[PDB]
Image: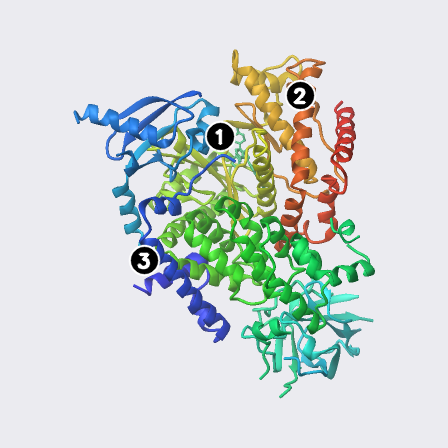
Amino acid sequence: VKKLINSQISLLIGKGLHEFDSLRDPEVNDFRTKMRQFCEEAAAHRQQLGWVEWLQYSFPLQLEPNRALLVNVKFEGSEESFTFQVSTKDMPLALMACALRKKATVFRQQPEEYALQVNGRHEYLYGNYPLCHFQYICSCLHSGLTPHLTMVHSSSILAMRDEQSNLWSLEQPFSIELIEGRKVNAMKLVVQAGLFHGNEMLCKTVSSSEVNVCSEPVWKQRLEFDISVCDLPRMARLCFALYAVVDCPIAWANLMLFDYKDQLKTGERCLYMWPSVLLNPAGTVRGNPNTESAAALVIYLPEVAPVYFPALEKILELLREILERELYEHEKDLVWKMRHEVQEHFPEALARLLLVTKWNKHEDVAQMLYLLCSWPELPVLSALELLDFSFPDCYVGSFAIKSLRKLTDDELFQYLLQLVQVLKYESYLDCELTKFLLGRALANRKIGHFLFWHLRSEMHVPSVALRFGLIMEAYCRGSTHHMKVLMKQGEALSKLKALNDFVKVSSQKTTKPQTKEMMHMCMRQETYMEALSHLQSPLDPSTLLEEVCVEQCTFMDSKMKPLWIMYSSEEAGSAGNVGIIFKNGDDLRQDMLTLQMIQLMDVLWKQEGLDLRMTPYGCLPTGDRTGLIEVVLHSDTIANIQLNKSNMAATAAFNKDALLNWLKSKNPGEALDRAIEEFTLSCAGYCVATYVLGIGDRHSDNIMIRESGQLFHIDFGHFLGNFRVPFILTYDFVHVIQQGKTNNSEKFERFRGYCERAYTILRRHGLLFLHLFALMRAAGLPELSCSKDIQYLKDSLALGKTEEEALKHFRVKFNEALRESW
Ligand SMILES: CC(=O)Nc1nc2ccc(-c3nn(Cc4cc5ccccc5nc4N4CCN(C)CC4)c4ncnc(N)c34)cc2s1
């Protein structure tokens, strides 16, 4: 039983648990038993949750950031239903109280014992909120549709829960012996080394003597470092680069100078190096696992006797404003002297003080830390900055995590991609970020879901495979049931991979109709119908994927041959008609990031009362160049529509009418007006988002429209101006915005306003994007690695300007776009 589970975990995470044992590594072992313990208690806590509290755990509320409506309501075990008319202002309780009246009359004769499930989804309506505040009711209003709900009794929710149970002495300089290696090249080889605390060096780098390429290299030399051993900060990182010269880089490697138990390191180490793209401070501090083939350096840390880092108990014993909103060396010195008044009267400037503190002198670090221990808790915004690699100290990190606990679950979810990436910066396996993510994920099943997937999707990256593998193991121990739910997902993804391979093979040797019918036969096999059916969507756990409609599935006959998979569900009706796209061969990470950023804009816009009718569709990497994109139904590409085919509702006398004609046929009579407004709002949002993000090569192939008028972007797949990208107005959208008239300055200028509001609201949260992109640097995305990428956002949001200033600047950009539009 505990052997079945171990095997289930092994299959789910894509790494066998026996591989953890074989490392005979006490840090891995200690991480495992402690994190198992932590996760088991969390699971125990959850099995006694109240029924409302469980709903909160398993089906967290989906909310928006007088008027009448129709609702259909039924009860759990009957098909008979009642249609009521209520107010968009009424709470779920009144509707429930209403539904119980109708039952008592029909069956010839307490609302608070129920919750309302959205039919055929894992989504529930409860709490003291007006119906219009629930994403679902809210969404229903905009599309016309009647909300459909089931009354579920508390006794039934509890049955769900139950079924789901489980020191300063050493004054001599620091130094190492560089012994030998075993490697491949073409000329002479040099080892260069630096001591780092984040990006900042703790002293100058020191180089090797030249030795010939023939090697199996030999050195037997002492590299001495210009810094007292008693000064090495807790998080001292020692870094190596091996290269050749008569410059040609070969490999690099890093390690911490203290182990995970705070002990200084001795004596001999063998470092298995990673291939190079010279010093790489940000690289992992674990050696290359491919030890058969990896070049290796042998070194020797010299025993100065054990020696540990001193307990905090010991450590605790031991024109300003005009600048405070990069600084000269005299400005630095001023801040440091003011550290106390910084604490008392500028607590939000912590980050700036941390960057001036001298991490290569131990006495100053004791100073800074002592101030940190009484430092007031900081705003989330400020805390997200502190998580950056320019703050490696474990005390700083703990303060940051401590400031971050006041994150709501909706916020945490919004920034989960970045917090996971920042695991790649960590020095050690057991850390505060890991416990934090595990804890919040075990308290919220939606967080759990995406945490799992963000980690699972990277298991083929050797630098994170062990770390990420271990976290998912701990997660599973805390939720046996959710483990199985995710296995169902992994098995579906495994079959889709097999199905996509067949399509790639078949389609090269036969015509599209022929392969299509083959795909269907392949899907109609028992093993497939079953593996592909009855799962939660990896794109959204509240979306249930029930019956694959084989007949509606296809593939696109191009490059990587992505698959199109439709689902239906009687229980959910029209709402359970949903689709996924499976893509294998392409990397989806950049698109996911882009889409999260756009969805962030939408939330920020909505919090100022601006709704730009965005389309934040699912996009999720699940494996090695593998993931999923959510089908947005009732949509088509601008290119396709602009083919202006005859025999169609939308056939134009002039190609420029095509897109308007299409909208007309989808939205007759008085419906046309709202579709044009939907188009205008959505167009403004994507124009501003693409501009702020530096995304170009937009064209009719990678823009789409919904039948409601909503325009949205797909397949980005470059950003931050690396292809300065101009603002873009396509004449074809301008034509539609203008209701089909040559001149319509009343409509075009309401459009300009939309853009100007959207843009000015983002500037107010400019720092949030900057902090978020800074952390994303951890992802290893080629287009998001250096500072010229961050600078791109600095320039697009004109953060160093006044709002009047930037708004004029933006107005020049917009007018330039208008001229470019024919
Ligand atoms: C790296 C990368 O590819 N990123 C990508 N991101 C996206 C995002 C969206 C889409 C996408 N593309 N399309 C058009 C489309 C894509 C198909 C993909 C695989 C198989 C069949 C496909 N058919 C598509 N159409 C074209 C329009 N037609 C009316 C319906 C079917 C979408 N339709 C609805 N929802 C979507 N989300 C899409 C594709 C991609 S690819």
Camera-side mark, 1 or 2: 2
Res. 229 image quadrant: bottom right
Q: Is residue 147 left or right of residue 624?
A: left
Q: Residue 267, position in %: x, y?
A: 61, 83
Near mark 3 (Cα within 10 A), the count class, few <14, some 14-19 or many ≥20, is some
Residue position marked by numbered label 1 in the rendering: 633
Q: Would residue 774 be visible to someone looking at this image?
A: yes
Amino acid type at mark 1: Leu
> How are the residues colored?
rainbow
Structural crowding at the residue carrying mark 1, measured as other residues with C-alpha within 10 Å and reported as few (<14), some (14–19) or many (≥20): few
Cβ of mark 1 under 8 A from ligand 1: yes
- Asked if the beta carbon under badge 3 is closer than 8 A to the nearest atom of ligand 1, the reply is no
Query: Which type of secondary structure does the marked residue at label 3 adopt?
Result: loop
Rendering quarter of residue 257: bottom right
| Secondary structure beneath label 1 | loop
Of badges 3 and 2, the one in the foreground is 2
- Disc 3/disc 1 C-alpha distance (Å): 39 Å
Amino acid type shown at disc 3:
Asn
- Nearer to us in this view, 210 or 206: 206
> Mark 1 and mark 2: span between their CA atoms?
29 Å
Q: N-terminal of the two: label 1 or label 2?
A: 1
Residue designated by label 2:
750
x and y percent of residue 655 in the render? 66, 18
**Image quadrant containing the C terminus:** top right
Res 166 label: 3
